[PDB]
Length: 62
Image 1: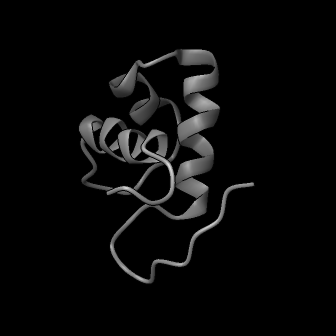
Image 2 (image 1 turned 90 degrees about the horizontal axis):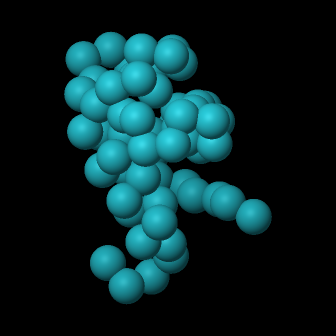
């Protein structure tokens, strides 16, 4: 289970696919993921780490 409904500048469910798809092999290698999978133009590798952070901060509390 993994759902959401934010109609604003955030990751699509497609980018979050590649996020975990990457980390599941890569481990925490963020620049590597950013290059390995198709992601939003003008991204930084931090955006991956930063979204991931909120993903592992789960629902509620934040």
